Length: 130
Length: 123
Ligand code: HEM
Ligand code: HEM
Ligand SMILES: [C-]#N
Ligand SMILES: [C-]#N
Image (tube, rainbow over all chains, first blue to last red):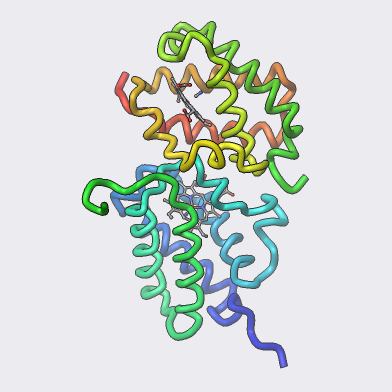
């Protein structure tokens, strides 16, 4: 009896569509994030839906088109501070709230994302964070 | 190919691409003054950075630590005009090394976004 994939567990394609569209809504309004993103977030949102789908055990949509994610490498030119990693996760938390993602699948997905976001950090903190 | 680094032609292509690029930089009046007179060490690091960025070996971070790319560019007066000059030199370098098609558009669009992020001084 097949357990559901995390992708299935979270609600599948329909949930990822709404989560990511909602997510980048928060990103576009966040002062710590919006400046480093492209002005139009459409292509970014499209790509993120492909990534999260495959990331959660759905079809390999991202790799099929774009090749290996190698996300840390792809984020190297961008100023990703621990502060911005925190803003990213904050927006995702709010998107998950808005999209009704809860329980064990929420904790599963959020904890993976938190680990990934930490991996992306490539610039040290501002004064105060020691 | 599974990585941009492979797709673009790998190490040999990055070599000629970056060597060519800094030839154009050295001749560009909007850029040459803020670069070192000798661009050897700069070209070396850029080959490391582009290699790792496009999915090759982690040459850059292994030697130099975290990228913190914008921070490394803060001490230089990088205007939008200079970002344009930078991208113009890269365009020519790509033409000269035969980088075309989708891999060209892929890499150039990412470099253009990056160059915009480096800007730290108004025109
Ligand atoms: C930690 C804070 C992060 C910041 C500040 C950040 C910022 C950015 C920016 C500015 C881009 C460029 C958008 C584009 O070129 O289309 C990007 C691309 C991308 N990021 Fe993030 N990112 C972060 C973390 C993450 C995380 C946790 C994930 C996990 C899903 C992720 C997945 C992606 C993907 C799939 C792309 C598209 C790359 C491509 O194929 O061109 N990023 N990121
Ligand atoms: C937007 C216009 C840009 C200007 C005017 C500019 C200018 C400079 C200058 C003057 C240096 C110092 C060179 C040295 O001290 O050896 C430097 C370093 C560097 N730049 Fe740029 N740059 C620009 C964009 C970029 C972009 C788009 C990239 C993408 C890879 C990049 C990657 C690097 C790297 C890897 C270094 C070496 C950092 C180190 O010392 O470890 N730069 N840049
Ligand atoms: C990355 N969003
Ligand atoms: C910098 N080139």
